[PDB]
Image (cartoon, rainbow over all chains, first blue to last red; front, side, top):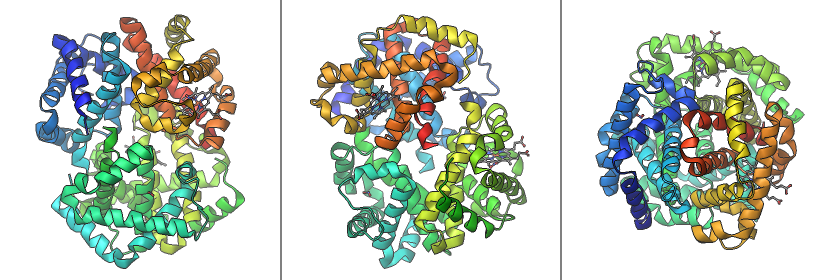
Length: 141
Length: 141
Length: 146
Length: 146
Ligand code: HEM
Ligand code: HEM
Ligand SMILES: O=N[O-]
Ligand SMILES: O=N[O-]
Ligand SMILES: O=N[O-]
Ligand SMILES: O=N[O-]
């Protein structure tokens, strides 16, 4: 359950991220692939080298999905339904992996938002990404 | 998201458990305390010895909560709201611990339901307990 | 992992009773059914579209037998799981990149299968001993990640 | 854990820059704020009712300093984390019964704090090296559970 304060915080952070959303998404993916090599096996057909146009393109899709979640924060299950279907049914993404990408998203925001990434906002973002992850794995429950 | 088949399965299993619900709940707790000793630190004031009236009494409360969830399976967040408040805010139960008790609940049902604990029903019960756990930890998201 | 002699007794006595031709396939089958993302690693097995398909799948039973063979081997060398599972770790970690949480899952599914098969014989202390064992095997299998 | 020399370089170079009087308390404070169930183990610290209270809490800063001191010690003995953290494991596992998932959490919070403090300097490879380190420390601290 995201509190009003959390929603305020998440919205503020996204605001500060602004038009870098896509680039930060690509950076989060690279952090994930390097830090947690097991995750790479979901993208055996991607080139995952630094600077990969495929990682950049995917980072944008991921960022777009998260912003759609922010923009429909009170209706996330519905907003993310197709994505939930895809990740669970087709891709069979191990639920553990959402924690890894969520962490890398936090790390990425932390490395870009010196002022915005306070302990409070960090907490709110964690809850947000946890909430998104819960939806994306819900086709497992 | 619990499917109609899952709801059917969970209801069937609870039916077979019948009036043993409380006793199985107490057994699940004992399994948890023995198997996962870290969990014992939430009950420092309980006597956790075998046959403890306090574990028996608590097992019944736990079983009652789960049956209330079954009985309001489409409204679990609302049904379990007070319990969610208690476990997160007051008790500060580590989320990992819900997986441990859920597993012990499955083990307990498995040891009591030779016919009922098929792979399908096992899957449905896992999802059910995962769904209950998600609600009970939701005051963390 | 250090089991007490009482824990070792609980484990050893039960295990002699295990149908080594069946329990492995039952545990693997259930893993694939209950945690369907695990099916990702076994697409070669064929029809896994339903529980019945999975449990009746001959490849599931056959591979499960090898898996249980590995557990048995760990049971024989509790005081050196690391050495025992070295090669399998290399395989699951370096080659397969299975997330280790899944080792813990298969271990807990195995526990469920033992509980189902042995019923009341699978007492809470016998379970607790088996939990130490499956944790130890999971940890050893995951060593190539450490 | 075996870091490559490149990984060791990434870790060592960054760490020399770390404010050992502050980062520990920042990581611990954030742990308590972000994963509030961890506050269960620190009721003696006093006011933890808000983020500001936690981060400004002198006990949080003081204990965090000791925690970071332990990380530093691990960094100095990467090829023997098990020996290094033996005593702390005994403490967190046998006496405190902290769930080890929480070790992984504190490690990841520390990573977040490093990212916040170092910004772009905390590159994805530097992160990946630090992830190996915090995993290794978590694993060693958890050894008394294995
Ligand atoms: C946790 C305890 C586990 C044990 C004791 C175990 C044991 C084994 C054994 C004995 C083999 C046969 C290796 C050989 O032919 O020499 C094997 C292969 C395999 N395992 Fe596991 N396993 C475990 C967990 C898992 C999990 C959780 C997964 C995936 C979800 C997995 C995926 C695989 C795959 C895909 C193979 C075939 C690899 C190949 O033939 O190249 N294993 N395992
Ligand atoms: C994961 C890496 C961790 C490291 C490196 C670490 C390090 C330390 C150190 C150096 C001390 C001081 C021990 C002494 O005074 O000799 C300590 C104490 C303590 N730690 Fe940790 N810690 C970690 C994780 C955790 C976590 C996640 C928790 C709980 C959520 C925790 C709970 C405690 C408590 C309650 C004490 C005080 C115990 C006492 O004074 O009796 N630790 N830790
Ligand atoms: O990278 N998540 O699609
Ligand atoms: O035992 N759960 O309250
Ligand atoms: O359990 N799969 O080897
Ligand atoms: O990090 N608490 O020691």
